[PDB]
Image (cartoon, coloured by chain):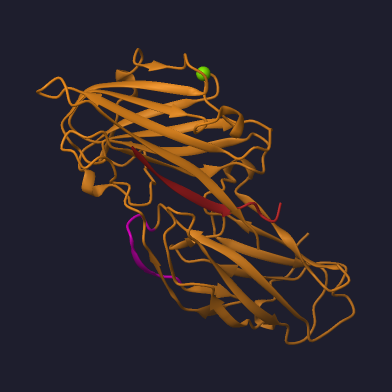
Chain colours: A red, B orange
Amino acid sequence: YGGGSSGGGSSGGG
Amino acid sequence: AKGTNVNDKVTASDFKLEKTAFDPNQSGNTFMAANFKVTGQVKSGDYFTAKLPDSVTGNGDVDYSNSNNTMPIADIKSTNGDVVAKATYDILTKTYTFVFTDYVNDKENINGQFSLPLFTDRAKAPKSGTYDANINIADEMFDNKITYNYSSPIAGIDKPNGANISSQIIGVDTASGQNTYKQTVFVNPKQRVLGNTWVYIKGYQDKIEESSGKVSATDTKLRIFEVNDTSKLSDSYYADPNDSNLKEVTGEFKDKISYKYDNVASINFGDINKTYVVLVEGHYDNTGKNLKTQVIQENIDPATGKDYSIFGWNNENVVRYG
Ligand SMILES: [Mg+2]
């Protein structure tokens, strides 16, 4: 039993 | 350096949003792309800007607060690799600033282009919906609308006494070298009647060796808040510790939190009947291994002493480039 979520963002090219 | 603001010499165009609807809770995001043009000429130091509405950000779940809220941005070039302009973005003012270099001093009618990631703003736009997303490039307004379709954090068993818990990693410090991360866990989003309730924050999922995360008493700070009205909670996972709707109760847990077992922390929620929020400030190592995590809750009881249950939840984030 379980679920999930993921996120996201910018490294700034680096 | 940074001399003049040449916006008035600058006219952007061919603006598009890669896409106008996504779920930021499944690594949804978009990109703004556009061409620009310099009516006339300029010099090393001049610059133009872009500014983002309340709805979007330019760093999403990558934190830069330990970097003077300044986000480096890959250089703007010509074909010979010549760095035409240097670029960065201010997390706070949501301002992109592109500042020319030793390259502009002998040319005119300049043309370039960018493509820049755009992410939700989890504080600004906390509930699934459509928002105005008017972006400014060189004092010209480009108007859009963004729809956020957050995967409800109200998730758990379908059982009336079912364990239910979610969580997101909403800020990661890649740049400072401090290697910190910020994570909101929601315990009992379903606000059910839950017996002897137990919670676990892991720095990994199934495999320790597969995550950079580190969860110890020394690497990890935790603040807990009883929620007043669950409906008032964000679909985005943002939680303002200063919301009146939250009551920090970190002082009721001095002896209910353990960093015994490896890369884990446990809270003893006991008998509960509403939602609680857990702010996580933790760190990950230099292994370069991705930062993956999982939180789990189990409850026993309630008013039967049997029908025990358990529900788990996984996080990791993705990096994009502009
Ligand atoms: Mg430990």
Question: The C terminus of chain B lies in which quarter of the figure?
Answer: bottom right
**Residue at position x 63%, y 81% from top?**
B12
Q: Camera-side residue: B300 or B174?
A: B300
Name which residue lies at 61% across and 74% down.
B33
Residue B46 x/y as whole percent: 75, 71
Q: Position of residue B206 (x, y in %)?
A: 50, 32
Q: Is residue B17 visible?
A: yes
Tell me if B191 is positioned left or right of B65 in this view.
left
The quadrant holding residue B47 is bottom right
Vertical relation: B289 (above or below) B60 = above
Residue B217 is at least partly visible in this image: no
Query: Could you tell me residue B228's position as x and y percent?
Result: 20, 38
Nearer to us in this view, B251 or B92: B251
The vertical placement of B94 against B220, above or below, is: below
Left or right? Give the position of B136 relative to B47: left
Left or right? Give the position of B14 relative to B54: right
Vertical side of B282 occupied by B111: above or below: below
Per the rendered image, the range of residues in magenta is B125-133
Q: Quadrant of the N terminus of chain B?
A: bottom right
In reply to whether residue B256 is colored magenta, the answer given is no
